[PDB]
Length: 140
Length: 140
Image 1 (tube, rainbow over the protein chains, first blue to last red):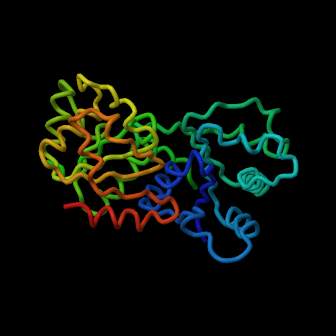
Image 2 (cartoon, rainbow over the protein chains, first blue to last red):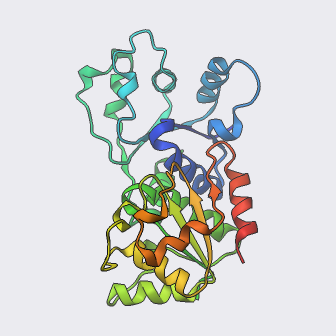
Image 3 (tube, rainbow over the protein chains, first blue to last red):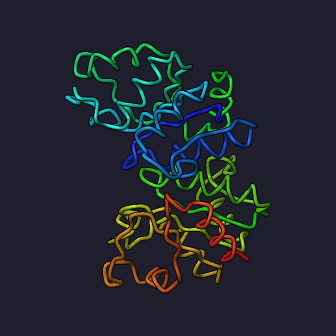
């Protein structure tokens, strides 16, 4: 059972999410990222189960990463779904900010507005080792 | 003296460049990337010497990565200068393609058109371990 789930937006956060996975694994964490560990079966169920299994929920906030959550009242966007699961389960949520513009909470669906109240970590290209160190400090 | 120099465009390939650095270091290669190894002094001298010192020249071709070299006739662009140094020294050049559109040689400065004759490796987000294994096979 992975200790860390990485939630990310494919068109903008795939490289940072993979970088996070490598570093966190190096430091002994079991990491779930879809390209490595999502296997056979119905992916909606499997992805929600993988969020529930992981104590830590790492959210890659690349530019525009929550755009597709906006107006997603039916909760059909996969990132929206992962965030709501992490919130409902009381996970240790750790946003990673990489060029992200913080939206006002009221443009997001009410069931995920609480994600903006968690302390985030700013990915520093120039100080990557220290960024990783900070993430590890935040993980449980 | 590091075995691998990583040349990349900061605005678009920083994440992939750092992902490549970590993976290659984990496989025992000594890697030069500016944010970790460029130290004090006049940076234009140091970066040229660093290209000269590394047997392998890993070129991160993220989207539009050569745009700033086009019509850079006085060769003031840093990626342009790094490529020219790699070609001039006959380094083992290994282009990494990630959403890159191959330009026609006419649009590039004459002293770097030869970079388009080297066999490149396509970055696959879904098959990253295989991509890394292929890069390692290309390295000397």
